[PDB]
Amino acid sequence: LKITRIDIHRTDLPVRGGVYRLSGGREYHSYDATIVSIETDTGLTGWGESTPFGSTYIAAHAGGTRAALELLAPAILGMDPRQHDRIWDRMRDTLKGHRDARAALDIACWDIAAQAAGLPLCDMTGGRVAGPVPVISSIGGDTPEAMRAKVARHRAQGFKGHSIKIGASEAEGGPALDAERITACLADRQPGEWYLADANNGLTVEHALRMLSLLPPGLDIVLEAPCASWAETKSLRARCALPLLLDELIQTETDLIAAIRDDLCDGVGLKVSKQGGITPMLRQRAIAAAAGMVMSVQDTVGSQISFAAILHLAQSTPRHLLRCALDTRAMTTAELAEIDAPLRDGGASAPSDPGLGLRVNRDALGTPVKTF
Amino acid sequence: LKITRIDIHRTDLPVRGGVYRLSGGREYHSYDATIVSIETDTGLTGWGESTPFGSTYIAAHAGGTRAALELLAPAILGMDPRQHDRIWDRMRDTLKGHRDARAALDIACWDIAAQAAGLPLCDMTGGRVAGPVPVISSIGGDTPEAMRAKVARHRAQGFKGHSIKIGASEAEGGPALDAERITACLADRQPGEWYLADANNGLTVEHALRMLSLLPPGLDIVLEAPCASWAETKSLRARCALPLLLDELIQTETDLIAAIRDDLCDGVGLKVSKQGGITPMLRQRAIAAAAGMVMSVQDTVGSQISFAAILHLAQSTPRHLLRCALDTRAMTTAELAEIDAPLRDGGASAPSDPGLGLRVNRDALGTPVKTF
Amino acid sequence: LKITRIDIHRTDLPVRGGVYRLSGGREYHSYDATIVSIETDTGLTGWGESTPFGSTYIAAHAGGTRAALELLAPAILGMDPRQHDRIWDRMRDTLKGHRDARAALDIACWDIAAQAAGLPLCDMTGGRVAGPVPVISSIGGDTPEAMRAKVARHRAQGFKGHSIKIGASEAEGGPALDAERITACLADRQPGEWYLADANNGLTVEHALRMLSLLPPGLDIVLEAPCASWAETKSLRARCALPLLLDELIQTETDLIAAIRDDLCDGVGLKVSKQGGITPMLRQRAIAAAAGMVMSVQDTVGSQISFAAILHLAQSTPRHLLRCALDTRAMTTAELAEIDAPLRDGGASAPSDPGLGLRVNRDALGTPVKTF
Amino acid sequence: LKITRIDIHRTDLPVRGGVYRLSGGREYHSYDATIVSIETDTGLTGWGESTPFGSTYIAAHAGGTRAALELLAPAILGMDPRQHDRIWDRMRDTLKGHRDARAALDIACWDIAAQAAGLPLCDMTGGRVAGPVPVISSIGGDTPEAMRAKVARHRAQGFKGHSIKIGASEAEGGPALDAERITACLADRQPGEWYLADANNGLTVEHALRMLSLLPPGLDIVLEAPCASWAETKSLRARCALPLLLDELIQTETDLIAAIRDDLCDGVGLKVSKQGGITPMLRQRAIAAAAGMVMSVQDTVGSQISFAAILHLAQSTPRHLLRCALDTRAMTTAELAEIDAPLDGGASAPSDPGLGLRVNRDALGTPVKTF
């Protein structure tokens, strides 16, 4: 079993709903996707998606993803796609970092390994955990009232978690606006829901502490990614009673080790293309699970191809530690593939078809930008 | 004085009341007890009980106790039952750990030593402290109002302490359910009571911090066994204002030292069969009292036999530090022995007779399953 | 695919070479082994072995292992043996701890999966890393001159690492003797060798610091398992410049996390049946690798069934962090299975056959003592 | 069983041998001993001794011991002497601290308990451990060359453990003198020997670090009681690879916990009348053994009566943690009682019920007080 051909495709994914806003005046109107197919000598095709949340979320951008694949793709031609640790080593030995580029390749290799074993990917990654995976919303920054409404649609649509973006500048209202945002987004809360306030590494410690003082007592909320640096996050941690989830700061396996060593956080936001694919998602899940860390299983953003990997990984994750999977279908307007995984009975369930369980609308991708 | 004969009995102890529920979906209908008699060349008989809380509470199960006794029982034959430290060392060089096994032998040797000295066990373990010992209930998991009613019944029986089992899954209602169980169980509080919220090692730190957030301010409560590991408990400890009591994680004397070195807790749940008998209970008492740690003197569960060891130990513990003895009679329905220790006048007083003070019902125990 | 039948075998494994000695007066003459076969509805057979190092190395003994299997083996009947994480989960909610009992079953389930897939276990566990794995001898306790000759004898056979067992009483010469056993064992050292001084949890901090003072400067040795407990190991660590490897103290994935949080060691002795099988070995490897900890891949002791498990895991471990695989063939005389894995070209290489690559000698294990 | 009478005695215990010097210019020619008997209504008699090492070793002196007994002894009239924790409680409720005074009472109560059970004390305190207990050779403050020769003497007589006293002022030679003494006393060492450098709380951190720097590499040595306070000792511990044993700083059970919490030492010097008798020696042992700390079992000083308590305690101690018992008979000339426990650098506790003492009541003088 051998990789013989890799094809790189590029497409645009339009935002669903308004401009997506994060802290620091970042705004996103659409997303540039890199979709990779991999073929074996035996005739299997694997699919992987990598789409940076534009160019300003972490140190990655779609054009960089493609430039890294120019090195990574030919490096792994003629390798056995089932030897996931050794493929990973070959990529590392080719090019340090650039996990966004590793991800699309790694996912497609896993998609193949699963099809070869005639198993859905959740049964290749530990085994299906019973019942559907609950799903989490992505609530762009807006006014408290507009945010609380986006929470309300998602609830009606059957979402159980909400990730509400915060991080208002002083000019915009500061910590008082963020505190109002949080109280408003929790106002219509019902039983069994879970809330995450995501600052996207955008708060000063001073702002976080002022926000925490303004929040009313007695709220059930988890703070995500409050600061831009490790040292800031450690200061806040010494002075914050709320659970803390790290996201942008946890990219590698050794970042997770640093967080354990410093007792930095109570949870991790694992994003498939941020961590670098299925392989590191599994290593990082194993580290986080040993540490008692809760895990929201996500991606930066993507199509149904990205969603498929998210759902399969979420579906083999211990329910005790899992804090929802991201439904990226709520996030863009695109239609790149078919997957049978609707929102019923509390969440989404991974399909039973071998591999990722996708039917890729190959005409929606356009002709490969590059082939190896 | 010399140990001549050791009999090993097996008997089932039914739960008093309905299903007993712990965190993690653990459910209990009855408990597999192992009762041991030890006989001397002077025709003294001593009794000791070890009953693991099924197979899922700590790394112990009844079949495991019996298999360990296959090693331990032959190894102490011929020893003077009065040389507690030398018997302890003989058990240790025969088999590491398995303190549930040591417990049964160890208790029966102390029962002998007390009888030979012509004193009740409490007067051999430092001396009776005046007045009855307050007793604590075990309030199994249920809805808040169901739990609240169980507390009422025990309060009416004259119980001063209540151990309330917490630890709901997200699907069950999560921290908010746990917060409601606590407030409900505390709702009819009268002066002089003491409450433990025991999660039996089943919270993530994320769940715990959310729960503590949800609790109203101004409660008098002790949190017990929140987390499944040392690193997780350390992390919560840094961010928790409530007294913390450790249970499952404190098994050896060296565990208590580690708890001191890391300032990990304010109190300890000492369980006769988890610590491994009267000898380690004494050493651990000494260590805890020096650290000004409060101690609740309990067992996993048991008949009147276990209750006798518990009560004598508590009866010789300083009142300043003692936070109840477990009335195991309120937990099980079985009558394996008679003991003169009614709840009245504030709690239960240890019998004045020599040894444990038990009149054992040999008929209730069945034919020995093994003899040495 | 479903597990249909589980057979449990008991045999005895005689020590190769003279009586094997450990710190604290422990001596081993033979080992009581538990061997498990597992059978699927498709007629595949898997094998696994678990043999505690007698009764006195960790809290484990063969009788307890067999007792635990009475709970575990029926628990997993009918499960798909390829779902390692859900099998693990089933085992943990049946019975806490007893990783020795999980190991035999866990390894047999991996054996099956590797067969079902048509792959050597090393290509199921990341991929074969090129070249033979260096093997480590096991130098039992004796006189400095006797130890130094055992080392010589293993060196002639092409062993590259040596684990030298230290830890003398004051009556036998204390620290100074240990310092002699080490200098002696290192005196015929050739290029490319690696030495561990293993005290098997048997030194006091006072003895270990005296020993360190006594050692001549300029030595290349790693200290292994110096002290009995977590708190003692931490005091030593604070005052010890030598790399330190932890063994008995690391059994669970959470133990390894605690070691990282406390910066307690530079390496870990992973033993297949102490960790509890292929599944936790892979989890602990991911944690150790992320932390940059070197790993010696070993087992307590075993036949060829134990050895196949070791060698397949070591063969897929990054060479950068590996610190030898234990060749159990030099520790015991038994021949319970056939395996084509000779010492040549610098160490042993995992066989190429599907699964463990064993030809088991089915009458050398004798009629099963229990079947489910 | 009831305590009916307590007699308090005072006798002087002349030094055996040369005048004993400690650090900071401390000097001693005889010791003021307090001996206590306790009688029960069944006619059993118990004996205990407490004798502070003059007036400057720790916060205790014989006149203070006796003033304290004036409160403590009447407090425990009427109690069952077997109820050691409740007697200890009564004593704490009566008078804070003064563990020297508790000691004499607590030891005599245990002596009774052991007699009433027909067991030697060692078998009341966990059970006899096999073999004799090593006893510690003491090497007084004096010149280096002199010191080494006294070690050669003690070695000749079969002693394997030596406690060597250090703590020279700058005038007298400073850390250099101390480094010389140590290197000397180890210079002709043989297999199986154990050495302790005892500063008796008298070094500054600066002195101690200069000493440690001036010492040759490769020495097997334990450092005892280097500094006068908790914070100084914590400073030195941060910068000291040598095993460290604490003595004067460890008096109560809570002292030992503070030591664990701070990771302050690897051993403790337990002294019967510093800790306060058998009851706290036993609590302290259990704490120390759980922490993996080695223990030297000693007393401040005393007659055979103090020796009996040390010896029964040492004899029930796990051997891998024990670092010698002290033979107080080598320290004083007093002949207050007979015990069959002769020395090979070693001694075994007698097999008689209780302490195994034949006390010469007359040798003690007329009680200074009766209750």
Image (cartoon, coloured by chain):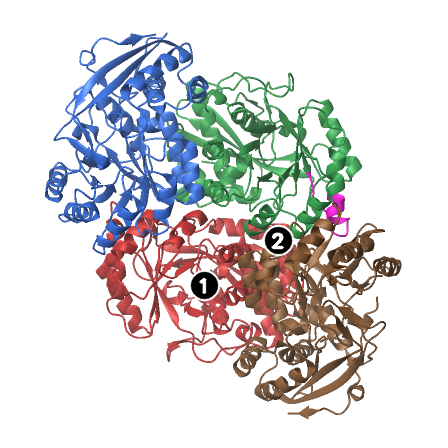
Chain colours: A blue, B red, C green, D brown
The chain under label 2 reads B
Query: Residue at the spot x=40%, y=22% of the render?
Result: C42
Could you give the CA–CA distance between mark 2 and mark 1, rounded to whole angstroms?
Answer: 32 Å
The percent position of residue B318, horizontal first and vertical second, equals 48, 73
Q: Identify the magenta region.
A: C165-178
- Give the camera-side residue of A326 and D171: D171
Direction from residue D6 to residue B11 in the image, left or right: left
Q: Which amino acid does label 1 sit on?
A: Ala
Q: In which quarter of the image is the C terminus of chain D?
A: bottom right
Query: Residue at the spot x=65%, y=82% of the render?
Result: D65
Mark 2, mark 1: which one is toward the viewer? 2
- Per the rendering, the mark at residue B364 is 1
The percent position of residue B4, horizontal first and vertical second, equals 65, 62
Q: Quadrant of residue D264?
A: bottom right
Query: Residue at the spot x=26%, y=69% of the render?
Result: B152
Residue A300 in view = yes
In magenta stretch: residue C142? no
The chain under label 1 reads B
- Per the rendering, the mark at residue B92 is 2
The percent position of residue B205, horizontal first and vertical second, equals 35, 48
In magenta stretch: residue C168? yes
Q: In this view, does D274 lie above or below B199?
A: below
The percent position of residue B134, horizontal first and vertical second, equals 40, 73
- Give the camera-side residue of C109 and A292: A292
* Residue lying furthest front: D171
- Per the rendering, the mark at residue D162 is none
- Give the camera-side residue of D363 and C153: D363
Secondary structure beneath dot 1 equals helix
Secondary structure beneath dot 2 equals helix
Residue D291 in view = no
Q: Which amino acid does label 2 sit on?
A: Arg
